[PDB]
Image: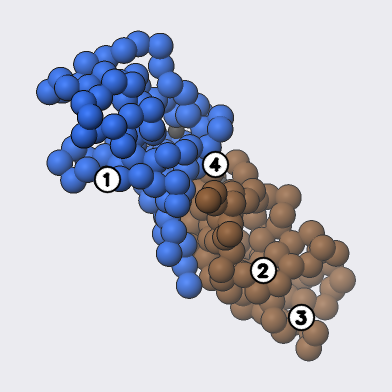
Chain colours: A brown, B blue
Amino acid sequence: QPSVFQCKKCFQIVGDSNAWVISHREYLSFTLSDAVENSVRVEDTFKRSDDGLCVYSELSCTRCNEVIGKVYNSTPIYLDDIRDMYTFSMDKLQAYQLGN
Amino acid sequence: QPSVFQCKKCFQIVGDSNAWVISHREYLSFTLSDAVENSVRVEDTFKRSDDGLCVYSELSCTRCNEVIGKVYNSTPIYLDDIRDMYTFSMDKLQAYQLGN
Ligand SMILES: [Zn+2]
Ligand SMILES: [Zn+2]
């Protein structure tokens, strides 16, 4: 049964499992191939990762302007699958699993 | 593909399809056999239907106190399928269909 993902603050649906790619328990994050277009804004600034191998732009929630994850623009070879995809911080989102 | 239903005001998920019973095109409403536990509050007043064949109590969104529908407590025999069941007003809700 699929889950839907929401901003924790305002409760805007950012996207669902189904468009899921991969999770990183190390990073405390998960990555979707797709997101709700109006719910999410990728910011117009490139920031250094902490490591700092990667380059990303923040994605903010459209409703409450929380920084809820990252779009990774440049990556090493091993982090290619999260590149140009929607990476959400677990800390910032909640999941609703459907019934039945 | 399933949908998920939220209050229009606060974005609280009140329930998903799958727990759906029936829809009425005439009155802008639909009916679910289930709702999210603390999502919804059924009020302490018995009100007459518009006809008024039925008796209902209002259901309110827990977070924002919007009247988003009705729990029909008493019905004629043909409207038994919606009795003791969660009837949401379409006007007060919004749907999110899952992708893929
Ligand atoms: Zn938000
Ligand atoms: Zn609400």
State the residue position of label 2.
A31
Residue A44: x, y in percent? Answer: 57, 67
For mark 2, give the secondary structure: strand
Few, some or many C-alpha atoms within 10 Å of disc 2 (few <14, some 14-19, many ≥20)? many
Q: Image quadrant of residue A52?
A: bottom right
Given the current orientation, which residue lies at the most extreme left position?
B51
User: Which is nearer the N-term, disc 2 or disc 3?
Assistant: 2
In-front residue for pair B12/A79: B12
Q: CA distance from mark 4 to mark 3?
A: 30 Å
- Quarter of image, ligand 2: top left
Residue appearing at x 45%, y 46% in the figure: B19
Q: Going from the N terminus, do you reach mark 4 or mark 2 first?
A: 4
Name which of mark 4 and mark 3 comes first in the sequence: 4
Q: Which residue is mark 3?
A: A79
> CB at mark 4 closer than 8 A to ligand 1?
yes
Above or below, B7 relative to B84: below
Residue type at mark 3 is Leu
Question: Is residue B37 found left or right of A25 in the rendered image?
Answer: left
**Residue A62 higher or lower than A32, as above or below:** above
Q: Amino acid at mark 1?
A: Ser
Residue appearing at x 62%, y 70% in the figure: A20
**Dots 2 and 3 on the same chain:** yes
Q: Nearer the viewer, mark 3 or mark 1?
A: 1
**Residue B22 is drawn in which quadrant?**
top left
The amino acid beneath tag 4 is Cys
**Between marks 3 and 1, how big is the CA–CA gap?**
46 Å
Number of the label disc, if any, that sits on residue A10: 4
Which label belongs to residue B23?
1
